[PDB]
Image (cartoon, helix red, strand yellow):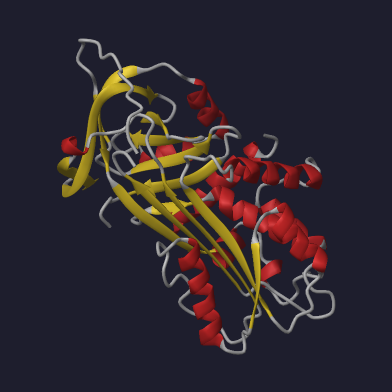
Amino acid sequence: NKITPNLAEFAFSLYRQLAHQSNSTNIFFSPVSIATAFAMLSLGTKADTHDEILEGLNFNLTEIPEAQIHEGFQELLRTLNQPDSQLQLTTGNGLFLSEGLKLVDKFLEDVKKLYHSEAFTVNFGDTEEANKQINDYVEKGTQGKIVDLVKELDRDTVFALVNYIFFKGKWERPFEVKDTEEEDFHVDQVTTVKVPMMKRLGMFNIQHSKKLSSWVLLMKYLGNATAIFFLPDEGKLQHLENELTHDIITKFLENEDRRSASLHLPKLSITGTYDLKSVLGQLGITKVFSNGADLSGVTEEAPLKLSKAVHKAVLTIDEKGAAGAMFLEAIPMSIPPEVKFNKPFVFLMIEQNTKSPLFMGKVVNPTQ
């Protein structure tokens, strides 16, 4: 897991930029899927174009050899795509290139073999049909979950990247649907809205963190992932966002102690759609999107730039997800603390093998 600290730093850098853009929107993105997509893209780039990409993913190229970078990503892809995965994690990256380009066979091999991704040739001279084929690929890859992803291409487009991911996890210790009820969600300190709220009395990996001024809940999925929910104390959301570090996360993941709690957690159906050109440009990745791009590993003779790059992540949290593991947790008599995720909170999903940050986000209003 040599690249996990870099991915964690990329997650935070990406998160802190989005939360600065808008402070009143649900955030949800996949640090892993975005970083995978552009590490794969870097294989077709050279010189500064290449270096800007890996540095933008929080890799110090003076310290970590590039072979270890791509080895880390491909080992991460090996665990996420096990055929016997209960993770129910659907992700894909599509490269759409102008059919008039002479593509380097080495790049297409690396994309399909090393990164298990997809590359398509399209006639960008028909800009509305190229857009349809891009949206059809995402809709077919998500079996109808993500529809009409790309809303507009510009006529000069010759190279587009789409990165999607959809997660519906199954809780190892599930909630009962009968106990889900409508509850208040404090969008601010004087305002509430009603949302469907799951609840369960059980033995939770849960603690209050002085450092973060937050409650910290860890719940395991069926499969190889854990969800971490951060509930900030009153007026402490910005403090929580500032203080998150990879080492603080690791200590939480090492704790296996359990205490009783009456947990209230909203059902969630949230999506995030991001312009990676704009977003990753703020993180230093710009030349690959500019006329000066060195994409000579993709095509040798003709000029090329990445004209379009979109990321869409979809999350569903509910009670269960297809029956009968039958865990019995023993609940002590004492009064269990009431931990209600009924105000803005942050969350992070972690791949259990690599400790990689599969997702990160913030819920400011479950029914936005």
Describe residue 149's horizontal placement relative to residue 66 as left or right: left
Above or below, comparing residue 199 to residue 32 in the picture: above
Above or below, comparing residue 121 to residue 349 in the picture: below
Describe residue 50's horizontal placement relative to residue 160 as left or right: right
Q: Residue at x 58, y 48 (%)?
A: 32
**Residue 184 coordinates in the image, percent (x, y):** 16, 43
Describe residue 348's horizontal placement relative to residue 38 as left or right: left
- In the image, 225 versus 208, the foreground residue is 225
As drawn, which residue projects farthest toward the bottom? 125
- In the image, 183 versus 326, the foreground residue is 326
Above or below, comparing residue 141 to residue 249 in the picture: below
**Residue 172 coordinates in the image, percent (x, y):** 39, 31
Asked whether residue 257 appears in the rendered view, the answer is yes
Q: Residue at x 54, y 40 (%)?
A: 84
**Residue 297 coordinates in the image, percent (x, y):** 81, 67
Above or below, comparing residue 160 to residue 209 in the picture: below
Tell me the quarter of the image containing the C terminus. Answer: bottom left
Q: Residue at x 34, y 23 (%)?
A: 204
Residue 39, quarter of the rendered image:
bottom right
Describe residue 192's horizontal placement relative to residue 7 as left or right: left
**Residue 325 coordinates in the image, percent (x, y):** 36, 27
Q: Residue at x 69, y 46 (%)?
A: 74
As drawn, which residue projects farthest toward the top? 333
Residue 295, quarter of the rendered image:
bottom right
Asked whether residue 22 appears in the rendered view, the answer is no
Tell me the quarter of the image containing the N terminus. Answer: top right
